[PDB]
Image (cartoon, rainbow, N blue to C red; front, side, top):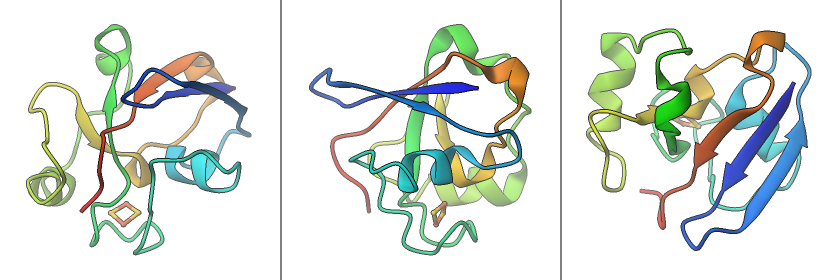
Length: 106
Ligand code: FES
């Protein structure tokens, strides 16, 4: 499944992620800039924050309270598109998924 990461300045990164991996790993394991992933996907740092593209938001599973609670600690979260990538699992049907990276991670 191809995952597309777009930095805030508009630089496009494309990665081929195997189903089962998380979006966070897809970016981390492939050297995509903008994702810190400090807690390693334990949904405790929120430094894997990103804005899912409006066109795909409805195709992802909805966020659980544990995740939503942690997004409020991310850098400039968006109630509509913000998500923690470590909480989104790649699946073949998400081939072509587009994610926009914030300017900073906290
Ligand atoms: S990488 Fe720590 S919250 Fe996702």
